[PDB]
Image 1 (cartoon, rainbow, N blue to C red):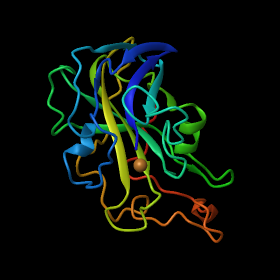
Image 2 (cartoon, helix red, strand yellow):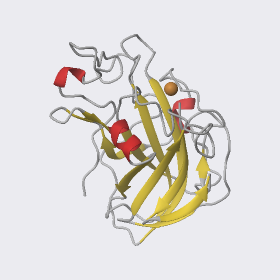
Image 3 (cartoon, rainbow, N blue to C red):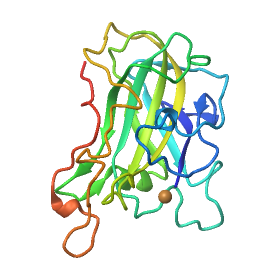
Image 4 (spheres, rainbow, N blue to C red):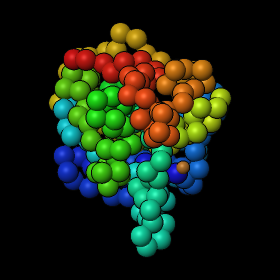
Length: 229
Ligand SMILES: [Cu+2]
């Protein structure tokens, strides 16, 4: 249970919920065919469009609730340690990131932090150690203009049952300057890109000793592979 609620651009804090379409509650989305998969549950919307340069170091901040820890010494801030899973970031080109409908967009993945089998480290593990932040560079080649920036935590602690994987998503409204001429060869739909039966969604991550180490096996994140310039 956590909410993507803040963006940083090359270390510059943009402010809580500034430029975000984020849910009001930290409850997970579990139906991969729901419209809630696009930007999380409908909650707060911002009029701000975050100005970014292609290649910038983007930070995405998860916290247990809106504003940080739910209470002093909250053990589930930024997110419960049991919630092992990947973190993924997608882009969708839109004309107007402040007014565009989240429905029917053409998404492509730009980054993911999934699972390292030799270190037994999940993307969520890195999120926790970075105090809720996940860091990734916008591709140098993406074209100028407005995008929705979709960041997604997929918690797999009870994903061994159908439809029980937990998704925590929000969208950031951005405008890219100094970009290139990249257009994705292929795009995916949200909802639609994920299926409940995907090997990275319907999965038992627990090993011999009951640890969430995926039995040291490689993990296949759902959706397309990250694009390359
Ligand atoms: Cu949770």
